[PDB]
Length: 233
Image 1: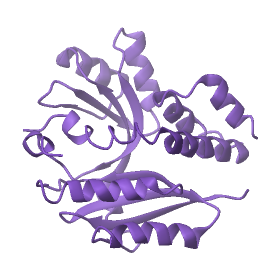
Image 2 (image 1 turned 45 degrees about the vertical axis):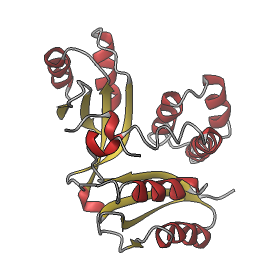
Image 3 (image 1 turned 90 degrees about the vertical axis):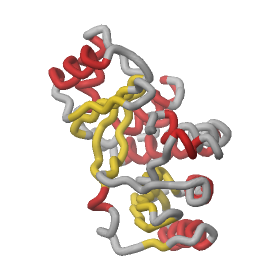
């Protein structure tokens, strides 16, 4: 009872309503990495920009910006006792932590020590196929170096790679006539947080408030959902 759109339907139907905020968070992550100009920190941003439909000239002009903002991560728990990580970028640490702290209060939750639920998360590249031949994609993926392949109930396919190889793998599948629909780099949970029609929209409200903050670059969670309940939100 677990499809891919079930853990991507909601919020992804909300992030496509806050495109200004999403566009501009990417911009800051591009400019800051170019100002660094550090290389393997620009790459990530660029890929995120593409997957979000940001034109090339726009990204190039952002990087071509090569205001002291720093990166900061937070951790906590939320609806249904669901683990959560928050990645930020800001020039004001205290204002950032307050806004993040405010979200949890308004959603019954609490931040924690830097090492709490983090160990429950592994940073890896994910190349997704919304459809296709499973055994052919799997072999081409493992062949290219992939670390694992997941096939969901809706035929969607997720290829996991070492976070820093998502690119080589993605390209291999393409040159092989096996184009992925998306290929990003996220934080994958090694555990499941069951959710009901009660502790889901509640969690989803937290992700919404957190993502509403301009300092919040990334929000990850293990609140696995089911097709059964996903049809209540």
